[PDB]
Image (cartoon, coloured by chain):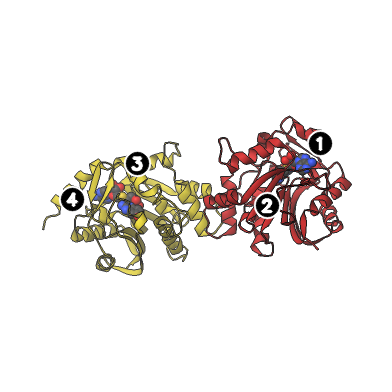
Chain colours: A red, B yellow
Amino acid sequence: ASAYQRFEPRAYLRNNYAPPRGDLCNPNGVGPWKLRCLAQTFATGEVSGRTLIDIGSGPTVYQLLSACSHFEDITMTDFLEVNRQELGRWLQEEPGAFNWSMYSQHACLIEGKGECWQDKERQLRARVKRVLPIDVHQPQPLGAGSPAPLPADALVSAFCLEAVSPDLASFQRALDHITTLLRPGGHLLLIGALEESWYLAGEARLTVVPVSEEEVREALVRSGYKVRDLRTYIMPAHLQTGVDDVKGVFFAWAQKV
Amino acid sequence: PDSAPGQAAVASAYQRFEPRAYLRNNYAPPRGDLCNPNGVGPWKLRCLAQTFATGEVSGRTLIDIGSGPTVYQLLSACSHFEDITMTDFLEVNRQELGRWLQEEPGAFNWSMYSQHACLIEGKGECWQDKERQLRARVKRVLPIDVHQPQPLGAGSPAPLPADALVSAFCLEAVSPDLASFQRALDHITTLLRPGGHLLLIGALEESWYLAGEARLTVVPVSEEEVREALVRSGYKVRDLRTYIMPAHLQTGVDDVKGVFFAWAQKVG
Ligand SMILES: Nc1ncnc2c1ncn2[C@@H]1O[C@H](CSCC[C@H](N)C(=O)O)[C@@H](O)[C@H]1O
Ligand SMILES: Nc1ncnc2c1ncn2[C@@H]1O[C@H](CSCC[C@H](N)C(=O)O)[C@@H](O)[C@H]1O
Ligand SMILES: Nc1nc2cc(O)ccc2[nH]1
Ligand SMILES: Nc1nc2cc(O)ccc2[nH]1
């Protein structure tokens, strides 16, 4: 935990969302794969509502691109002030924001509605109402009188839980905690590392609980979800970069029942 | 009558043509705004993309007639031709294309056009791939004069005859009158093999446009005039569609009232 105090957002982005992992040109890369699960899922039309919460956003937005066209009130979160400040730099188009434009374009490409990436970024920036602090370790992760409309119609979290959880059970509880934020019938789209144990973010060196596809499945069931979709991307050699030791990436579409 | 005087007036006026001012006037926003699907930019890209998408327009070689400082007209095309020749009358335009080819920062940025084409061709291509291909397939940039009977010169580089021709806002913009236009059309048509295809785009009912200092003169033409010239030069007209310029895209850089797109195949 205290490890996250040393977490450098620029180094995290550089490590994961700049080339080689950040190169979206090759359709066999992790980035293209991630956007596709997101897009495909929403394209079904079955994940819809008015409000949505992104759990542990860090300093990234890609995870909301296809999503933002289906929910008018979007709430983003993270445990670190630094990250929240970085999200705001891109939301307010302030100086030194991160360049998500490749990711916007590709989302537009994948969705195939002939939308221009500028329109896409405009819509995201418009629907994100607030950026709130959060701790998944708390049975009320948002706090008491959170400005966020609860319960949310749907939830999105990527590379969070397993990254803030020392072991399998703390993972399971964190999932339970957030699940409380989700209106019954609501949907959860969860993405994360498979069989990862550590990863760097500058001077920070975070520990991770190595999970598996089955382990992730079981957890979702245990938390009270019907698992609608669960897919795995195996990390190609050339995307093993020594910023971490992730072996694969998983995507789950889960429905609170 | 006499072609020389008119042709000389043209050549004279174009010595004042400023490529940057031209680029800004027509390919920066509001005209350059690709976000609105009702815009001219999107309509043009869509005409090209849909056309090549039939798969009916292919081969080894292609020539772009009066490229000017622009490449957007080749984005959907370059996936279908190994060898592409670009051409323009003015050297300063040829140099402008040179900058883009060398991928210099000084160059004009077409990335929005590349992105949008990729977007409409629907193959999830990334724009950098599309651009890298175009630069790969442009085998030369040649001087051209459509008023000569051999618009490229004699014994010129271009592999002739070409399997297809592309030309956008060229003919009507260098032709003082309909007869000149027609002749220019016949001259370039000698570069196209029989059975080959011509994709033609240009202004409808336009008489002038600005390119910096240069306020140039254009022969206003209509859809039907364009149709007839094609028939006259020996083309079956496969498709001819018209875009009516929206009030808010009529910005005083010209007096264009519409834009025409012609897919025509040379009888052979
Ligand atoms: N106790 C906690 N509760 C919620 N998030 C936490 C947390 N402790 C750390 N985090 C955050 O978990 C994030 C993991 S990195 C994930 C970034 C982004 N979702 C992406 O898809 O890349 C970090 O931003 C980190 O600050
Ligand atoms: N006699 C001639 N023969 C062929 N092209 C000529 C010409 N005289 C002028 N031109 C060129 O005609 C161009 C018209 S502007 C069109 C540029 C580009 N094709 C577009 O799509 O915007 C100018 O670049 C000009 O140099
Ligand atoms: N922690 C973390 N590991 C990752 C691996 C990826 O391939 C993409 C995003 C990531 N985030
Ligand atoms: N000359 C010229 N006129 C034009 C009109 C347009 O709408 C787009 C490009 C052009 N080029």
Q: Quadrant of residue A243?
A: top right
Q: Is mark 3 within 8 Å of ligand 2?
A: no
x, y percent for residue B38: 43, 60
For disc 3, the chain is B
Residue depicted at x 24% and y 46%: B215
Kindly identify the amino acid type of the residue bearing the numbered disc 1.
Answer: Ala
Residue that label 4 marks: B7
How far apart are labels 3 and 2 at the CA level? Answer: 40 Å
Residue B20: assigned label: 3
What's the chain of the residue with tag 2? A
Q: Which residue is mark 1?
A: A1
Tell me the kind of residue under disc 3.
Answer: Arg
Q: Is mark 2 within 8 Å of ligand 3?
A: yes
**Of the two numbered discs 3 and 1 in the rendering, the one whose residue sits closer to the viewer:** 1
Q: Amino acid at mark 2?
A: Lys
Q: Label 4 crowding class (10 Å Cα cut-off): few <14, some 14-19, many 20+? A: some
